[PDB]
Image 1 (tube, rainbow, N blue to C red):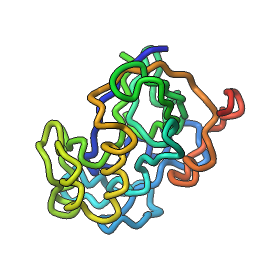
Image 2: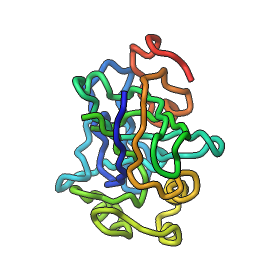
Image 3: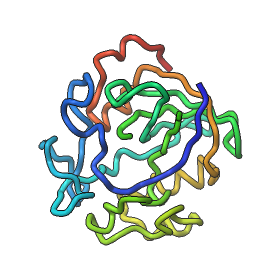
Image 4: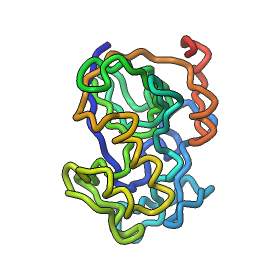
Length: 205
């Protein structure tokens, strides 16, 4: 299947972090304002007034080698639903921009075929959970930061994911890709805690 990508980081509790959404062992972990995991999956989202639950900093992308990376996304898949995509994994092959030919495996943690890649500094967009969490992130509300040096001012836990945008991803602007559903790698489930009961039905990478 073919799709288009965008980038974001709004600090909000991810949509697959609520119970009863999908056939999983446990929902995706949320974190408090100090980036520590919390065990109450019913906790109120930090993107609503009085809320306490935010996105965790370890749900960020990294490079395995120059041609392969791992990470997370908010997904919409044509004809499917949250029960089908929450905590599912997908292999992306980029087909445009400076990353053409490179591959990435992502786990869906939140909600046409469109993948919004989790990238600190990609832009908060409609909801700004980062201002209540810790005072806000640098960048334009829509579009985020523009140069690698602006990552230097981010909280230390979010720096690795910020630099990945410039280093491995070559500052690509919304590249297109082809994708397929795959079994989640262990490294991704270790970060979110969320494994689907149907993961034995898909090929491995």
